[PDB]
Length: 262
Image (cartoon, rainbow, N blue to C red; front, side, top):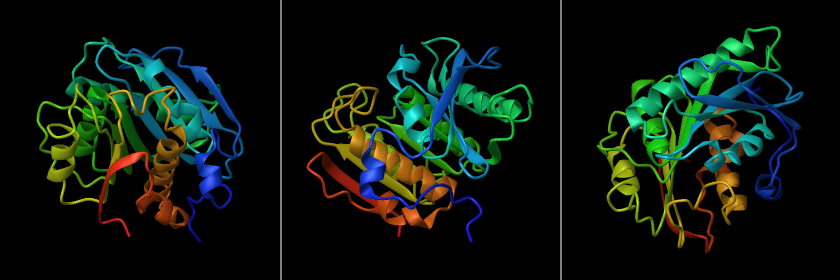
Protein backbone atom coordinates (compact mmCIF):
# COMPACT_ATOMS: atom_id res chain seq x y z
CA UNK A 1 0.00 0.00 0.00
CA UNK A 2 1.23 3.54 -0.74
CA UNK A 3 1.35 5.42 2.62
CA UNK A 4 1.09 8.79 0.84
CA UNK A 5 -2.01 8.11 -1.28
CA UNK A 6 -4.79 10.48 -0.19
CA UNK A 7 -8.40 10.93 -1.20
CA UNK A 8 -10.73 9.12 -3.57
CA UNK A 9 -9.61 7.62 -6.84
CA UNK A 10 -9.31 10.37 -9.46
CA UNK A 11 -11.40 10.87 -12.57
CA UNK A 12 -10.89 13.35 -15.39
CA UNK A 13 -14.07 15.03 -14.18
CA UNK A 14 -12.91 15.31 -10.57
CA UNK A 15 -9.53 16.73 -11.68
CA UNK A 16 -11.11 19.24 -14.06
CA UNK A 17 -13.56 20.65 -11.48
CA UNK A 18 -12.74 23.95 -9.79
CA UNK A 19 -12.21 22.18 -6.46
CA UNK A 20 -11.26 18.67 -5.37
CA UNK A 21 -12.92 16.57 -2.67
CA UNK A 22 -11.44 18.21 0.45
CA UNK A 23 -12.64 21.32 2.24
CA UNK A 24 -10.08 24.16 2.12
CA UNK A 25 -9.36 26.72 4.80
CA UNK A 26 -6.70 29.42 4.69
CA UNK A 27 -4.88 31.89 6.88
CA UNK A 28 -2.45 34.77 6.48
CA UNK A 29 0.99 34.07 7.94
CA UNK A 30 1.33 36.38 10.94
CA UNK A 31 5.11 36.97 10.85
CA UNK A 32 6.66 35.87 7.55
CA UNK A 33 10.24 34.76 8.12
CA UNK A 34 12.45 35.32 5.08
CA UNK A 35 9.85 36.52 2.58
CA UNK A 36 7.29 39.26 2.20
CA UNK A 37 3.90 37.77 3.02
CA UNK A 38 2.13 34.44 2.80
CA UNK A 39 -1.27 32.79 2.67
CA UNK A 40 -1.47 29.12 3.64
CA UNK A 41 -4.26 26.91 2.27
CA UNK A 42 -4.91 23.52 3.83
CA UNK A 43 -7.36 20.61 3.61
CA UNK A 44 -9.44 19.20 6.44
CA UNK A 45 -9.27 15.44 7.15
CA UNK A 46 -7.12 14.43 4.18
CA UNK A 47 -6.55 11.03 5.79
CA UNK A 48 -2.93 11.54 6.81
CA UNK A 49 -0.21 14.15 6.62
CA UNK A 50 0.19 15.82 3.22
CA UNK A 51 3.01 17.43 1.28
CA UNK A 52 3.59 21.16 1.06
CA UNK A 53 3.90 23.38 -2.02
CA UNK A 54 5.30 26.94 -2.14
CA UNK A 55 4.20 29.20 -5.00
CA UNK A 56 5.92 32.45 -6.04
CA UNK A 57 4.63 35.14 -8.46
CA UNK A 58 6.57 36.97 -11.16
CA UNK A 59 8.43 40.25 -11.51
CA UNK A 60 6.25 43.15 -10.25
CA UNK A 61 3.46 40.67 -9.35
CA UNK A 62 1.83 39.62 -6.08
CA UNK A 63 -0.09 36.63 -4.72
CA UNK A 64 -3.23 37.58 -6.69
CA UNK A 65 -1.56 36.40 -9.89
CA UNK A 66 -1.03 32.80 -8.64
CA UNK A 67 -3.65 32.64 -5.87
CA UNK A 68 -6.01 30.26 -7.71
CA UNK A 69 -3.50 27.42 -7.25
CA UNK A 70 -3.95 27.55 -3.48
CA UNK A 71 -7.52 26.30 -3.19
CA UNK A 72 -7.15 24.13 -6.29
CA UNK A 73 -4.16 22.15 -5.00
CA UNK A 74 -5.18 22.10 -1.33
CA UNK A 75 -8.61 20.70 -2.13
CA UNK A 76 -6.88 17.57 -3.47
CA UNK A 77 -4.70 17.08 -0.39
CA UNK A 78 -1.76 19.51 -0.15
CA UNK A 79 -0.78 22.36 2.11
CA UNK A 80 -0.02 25.31 -0.15
CA UNK A 81 1.67 28.60 0.70
CA UNK A 82 1.39 31.47 -1.78
CA UNK A 83 3.88 34.22 -1.08
CA UNK A 84 4.69 37.82 -1.77
CA UNK A 85 8.38 38.50 -2.09
CA UNK A 86 10.34 41.03 -0.04
CA UNK A 87 10.30 43.22 -3.14
CA UNK A 88 8.26 42.77 -6.30
CA UNK A 89 11.55 43.44 -8.16
CA UNK A 90 13.36 40.41 -6.68
CA UNK A 91 15.19 38.27 -9.25
CA UNK A 92 14.89 34.45 -9.57
CA UNK A 93 17.79 33.53 -7.23
CA UNK A 94 16.24 35.66 -4.48
CA UNK A 95 12.76 34.29 -5.24
CA UNK A 96 14.23 30.80 -4.80
CA UNK A 97 15.62 31.68 -1.35
CA UNK A 98 12.26 33.10 -0.32
CA UNK A 99 10.43 30.05 -1.69
CA UNK A 100 12.57 27.71 0.40
CA UNK A 101 12.11 29.99 3.43
CA UNK A 102 8.33 29.81 3.00
CA UNK A 103 8.52 26.00 2.95
CA UNK A 104 10.66 26.11 6.09
CA UNK A 105 8.06 28.26 7.82
CA UNK A 106 5.30 25.84 6.81
CA UNK A 107 7.37 23.14 8.52
CA UNK A 108 7.64 25.34 11.62
CA UNK A 109 3.89 25.98 11.66
CA UNK A 110 3.39 22.21 11.38
CA UNK A 111 5.23 21.91 14.70
CA UNK A 112 3.31 24.81 16.32
CA UNK A 113 0.32 23.63 18.36
CA UNK A 114 -1.50 26.97 18.05
CA UNK A 115 -1.34 26.77 14.22
CA UNK A 116 -4.26 25.50 12.10
CA UNK A 117 -1.91 23.17 10.18
CA UNK A 118 -0.41 21.67 13.35
CA UNK A 119 0.49 18.08 12.48
CA UNK A 120 -1.05 18.24 8.99
CA UNK A 121 2.17 18.41 6.91
CA UNK A 122 4.71 15.77 5.93
CA UNK A 123 7.76 18.04 5.88
CA UNK A 124 9.83 15.45 4.00
CA UNK A 125 7.67 15.95 0.87
CA UNK A 126 7.79 19.42 -0.70
CA UNK A 127 7.17 20.96 -4.11
CA UNK A 128 7.75 24.30 -5.79
CA UNK A 129 5.71 26.29 -8.30
CA UNK A 130 5.74 29.81 -9.62
CA UNK A 131 5.16 32.17 -12.51
CA UNK A 132 7.78 33.79 -14.77
CA UNK A 133 10.72 34.84 -12.54
CA UNK A 134 8.94 32.90 -9.80
CA UNK A 135 9.02 29.92 -12.15
CA UNK A 136 12.69 30.54 -12.79
CA UNK A 137 13.09 30.61 -9.02
CA UNK A 138 11.32 27.25 -8.69
CA UNK A 139 13.80 25.66 -11.09
CA UNK A 140 16.62 27.20 -9.09
CA UNK A 141 15.04 25.76 -5.91
CA UNK A 142 14.93 22.40 -7.60
CA UNK A 143 18.52 22.62 -8.87
CA UNK A 144 19.76 23.60 -5.42
CA UNK A 145 17.48 21.31 -3.36
CA UNK A 146 17.13 17.88 -5.03
CA UNK A 147 15.23 16.64 -1.95
CA UNK A 148 12.21 18.48 -3.43
CA UNK A 149 9.69 16.00 -4.81
CA UNK A 150 8.23 17.99 -7.73
CA UNK A 151 8.27 21.31 -9.55
CA UNK A 152 5.65 22.89 -11.84
CA UNK A 153 6.74 26.37 -12.98
CA UNK A 154 4.60 28.29 -15.45
CA UNK A 155 5.96 30.54 -18.23
CA UNK A 156 9.35 30.36 -16.50
CA UNK A 157 12.04 32.95 -16.98
CA UNK A 158 15.62 32.73 -15.82
CA UNK A 159 18.82 34.44 -16.89
CA UNK A 160 20.48 31.10 -17.69
CA UNK A 161 18.39 28.31 -19.23
CA UNK A 162 20.88 25.58 -18.27
CA UNK A 163 19.13 23.39 -15.70
CA UNK A 164 20.92 20.21 -16.72
CA UNK A 165 21.62 19.30 -13.09
CA UNK A 166 17.93 19.07 -12.12
CA UNK A 167 16.82 15.63 -10.88
CA UNK A 168 13.40 16.81 -9.61
CA UNK A 169 10.26 15.83 -11.62
CA UNK A 170 9.48 19.06 -13.42
CA UNK A 171 6.36 20.08 -15.34
CA UNK A 172 6.83 23.24 -17.41
CA UNK A 173 3.69 25.13 -18.39
CA UNK A 174 4.42 27.39 -21.36
CA UNK A 175 2.31 29.96 -23.20
CA UNK A 176 2.57 29.66 -26.98
CA UNK A 177 2.53 33.40 -27.78
CA UNK A 178 4.50 34.56 -24.74
CA UNK A 179 6.25 37.79 -25.75
CA UNK A 180 7.74 38.38 -22.26
CA UNK A 181 9.43 35.00 -21.66
CA UNK A 182 9.25 33.66 -25.24
CA UNK A 183 8.92 29.88 -25.38
CA UNK A 184 11.75 29.51 -27.90
CA UNK A 185 14.27 31.31 -25.66
CA UNK A 186 12.99 30.51 -22.15
CA UNK A 187 10.57 27.64 -21.42
CA UNK A 188 11.70 25.35 -24.21
CA UNK A 189 15.51 25.72 -23.79
CA UNK A 190 14.95 25.15 -20.07
CA UNK A 191 13.02 21.96 -20.80
CA UNK A 192 15.60 20.82 -23.37
CA UNK A 193 18.46 21.22 -20.89
CA UNK A 194 17.12 18.66 -18.37
CA UNK A 195 18.15 15.07 -19.20
CA UNK A 196 18.19 13.55 -15.67
CA UNK A 197 14.57 13.79 -14.57
CA UNK A 198 10.99 13.01 -15.26
CA UNK A 199 9.78 16.09 -17.07
CA UNK A 200 6.97 17.46 -19.17
CA UNK A 201 6.41 20.47 -21.40
CA UNK A 202 2.85 21.69 -21.93
CA UNK A 203 2.36 24.71 -24.19
CA UNK A 204 -1.01 26.46 -24.00
CA UNK A 205 -2.42 27.16 -27.46
CA UNK A 206 -2.67 30.89 -28.15
CA UNK A 207 -1.54 31.73 -24.61
CA UNK A 208 0.05 34.99 -23.56
CA UNK A 209 2.48 35.29 -20.65
CA UNK A 210 -0.34 35.15 -18.07
CA UNK A 211 -2.10 32.10 -19.58
CA UNK A 212 -1.82 30.11 -16.33
CA UNK A 213 -2.50 32.91 -13.85
CA UNK A 214 -5.58 33.42 -11.70
CA UNK A 215 -8.66 33.78 -13.88
CA UNK A 216 -7.17 32.08 -16.94
CA UNK A 217 -9.49 30.33 -19.38
CA UNK A 218 -7.79 26.92 -19.13
CA UNK A 219 -8.22 26.23 -15.43
CA UNK A 220 -9.79 22.83 -16.08
CA UNK A 221 -6.81 21.51 -18.03
CA UNK A 222 -4.03 23.43 -16.27
CA UNK A 223 -5.43 22.55 -12.85
CA UNK A 224 -5.89 18.90 -13.81
CA UNK A 225 -2.27 18.65 -14.97
CA UNK A 226 -0.84 20.49 -11.98
CA UNK A 227 -2.75 18.42 -9.44
CA UNK A 228 -1.96 15.17 -11.29
CA UNK A 229 1.74 16.00 -11.52
CA UNK A 230 2.00 16.86 -7.83
CA UNK A 231 -0.01 13.79 -6.78
CA UNK A 232 2.06 11.52 -8.99
CA UNK A 233 5.43 12.76 -7.78
CA UNK A 234 4.92 14.25 -4.33
CA UNK A 235 2.75 11.31 -3.21
CA UNK A 236 4.26 8.70 -5.59
CA UNK A 237 0.59 8.07 -6.35
CA UNK A 238 0.45 5.78 -9.37
CA UNK A 239 -3.30 6.31 -9.60
CA UNK A 240 -2.23 9.56 -11.26
CA UNK A 241 0.33 8.06 -13.63
CA UNK A 242 -1.87 8.48 -16.70
CA UNK A 243 -3.20 11.92 -15.79
CA UNK A 244 0.30 13.16 -14.93
CA UNK A 245 2.13 11.72 -17.96
CA UNK A 246 -0.46 11.63 -20.78
CA UNK A 247 -0.71 13.94 -23.74
CA UNK A 248 -4.09 15.62 -23.02
CA UNK A 249 -5.03 15.42 -26.73
CA UNK A 250 -6.66 18.81 -26.49
CA UNK A 251 -7.13 21.79 -28.77
CA UNK A 252 -6.01 23.96 -25.85
CA UNK A 253 -2.47 22.51 -26.17
CA UNK A 254 -0.20 23.61 -29.00
CA UNK A 255 2.88 21.56 -28.06
CA UNK A 256 3.35 18.56 -25.75
CA UNK A 257 6.59 16.83 -24.77
CA UNK A 258 7.44 14.45 -21.96
CA UNK A 259 10.36 12.29 -20.88
CA UNK A 260 10.81 9.53 -18.29
CA UNK A 261 7.04 9.61 -17.56
CA UNK A 262 5.46 6.17 -18.13
